[PDB]
Length: 330
Image (cartoon, rainbow, N blue to C red; front, side, top):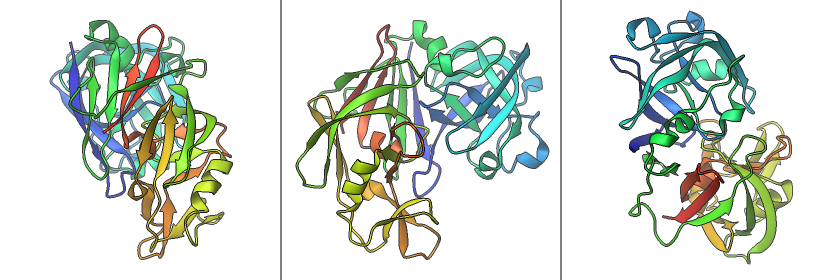
């Protein structure tokens, strides 16, 4: 079996992507943020504190004939941006683009932090990292991908994110028409629960490629590309007036600049991020300072190949016994 669903940017900056997901019987369609950097499928629900819900569509397990309380199970998760959520757990039928998993753990939010409440278009998250990161206690739960895996034609999912445009998440197959050239596969470490891999280097604009190992995670749930301070300073040094601002929380550049491209290595292959993908617009409306799409990973503890990088490629998340990541130009 296979699944295919369209993913759409939530705003004019590609701050996040939402993908419709059907939950329960009759179906309740929620728009979830597919996140390869977490492993919990959680939703805004009829149990979420009324003052913490602002425009979101909620999951009502009492209206689903297939919902069952996962008795005693609770979840509690904190994300790198400081946001958090917690609640109880149900099992229900979950379908993504025609691919159905019965008995999927659906983590109902009892509490969400302000960052979740204010994103009216995001009804929850669908975790696609390894199930070892799942926060369900005392019985740890499997992701939608993990649960679907045996039924899939191929144990894979692919992320084809668009730049200011919709894209696609495919499950169980590789669409050979969605990319050009070949897909370069690279080793994955599952030791921290992430799609953690090693980039072979980088180039800034038309500059020469520097062969250097950069460990990092392929994370659809992170908007920007976070890399070591050395790499990020070398990129922003090519943009006149660009500087790192402590008041803004990162690198900004004059909105009048035309940004150079950024190339990252995947084995002997190269993925080119056009300069336009690195422009996140004015820091505040009307501002002449624009926010950079490439930021330092210094305060995080891990390098993150977020949407800025992933949207420049057709990306394969190979969940076979020995997991690998595939990258192709598109």
